[PDB]
Length: 402
Ligand code: HEM
Ligand SMILES: COc1cccc(OC)c1O
Image 1 (cartoon, helix red, strand yellow):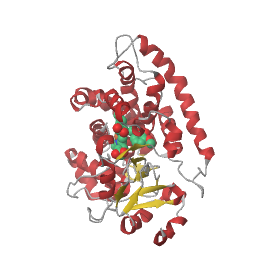
Image 2: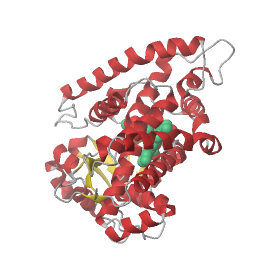
Image 3: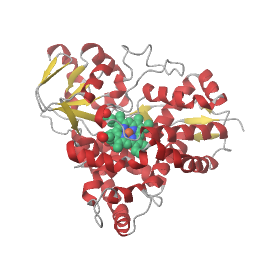
Image 4: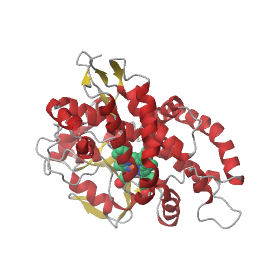
């Protein structure tokens, strides 16, 4: 497309370090645009992302690097009967009435345990010391991975992240960094070595762990889902479900720190924490551009006539800065009027764990502010955000008196 020739010079590193300038141009010039280094059409505005994610003429497809990382059948990448089965598999523990039965007793003691290690230090790096540990320890226990240390869960989601977002392609559409999948493969090998004996045990001795229920739920007597059938969705969990609540917590904190007067409001009135988190997710969406759909027939989107079989990456993080919806979206604003956002996606492949994730982030922030009410950010340190597929702050140094 001739007038978008500047897109030929957009690099993967540029999109990873800060995609917002390129995507501001995309939202104005071409809400649906083919980005050469990603090898795909990308949807950048709220209208186009929502349309593609809910269209009867699109279905789920995994991004190329995500498919290389997860294989088949990843819940995010399949449709029809297989997707219906995988959704029925994961949904029980995520049902709101079910989450409300045990979420407090799950997350609150975990939050306190990680806080107790540093709440009197006067300094902390909250991404590694708090946000990621609470996120992974909560989900890990729910899944049945109690004996997998939070360091290991965090390492796995970091390697899966880099593998599943290893999207750069060369002139011929081939992956430009083929060695970047190796640490994904390696993480998967480690995961198998840990999880295979757990599955062996759960097949014979089911328990209340989520993965045990994934094996057994809805199955004829004496049968379990084959482990090869559920492992790709285990990997989906061990990337985004492990990573995103921690990133959403951390981005919300960075946003609040940028508005000191709003941090103070929320600490004074913790009933504002859900609103603070909702704005945090819009402001820096944890899942920024990690999923996609594929057209199933010829379809016209944003004036582009797409053939059948055309993938479209859903850059929800860009859609959540759509100035057709938001005023000054690059600024964190607790007092933004509550509007729909796309940080959980849309359509039949929208996030299945919204209610759980919101509670994990809420409880974690409640306990943090109770333990450290005079929390401040360490302004001697910069906060850098990283990621195009998944985005969040790489560190969050804080300080407090005493
Ligand atoms: C703040 C934290 C989270 C955010 C921002 C988030 C966001 C998202 C997004 C954007 C998608 C893709 C939706 C689309 O393509 O339209 C997704 C899919 C999904 N998420 Fe969440 N997620 C979070 C946490 C979680 C957690 C903790 C779990 C599990 C306990 C979870 C389970 C899933 C599943 C199973 C899918 C795939 C749904 C499908 O393809 O049918 N998510 N999430
Ligand atoms: C590409 O990987 C993912 C995309 C969307 C959601 C995920 O975990 C919930 C996830 O792991």
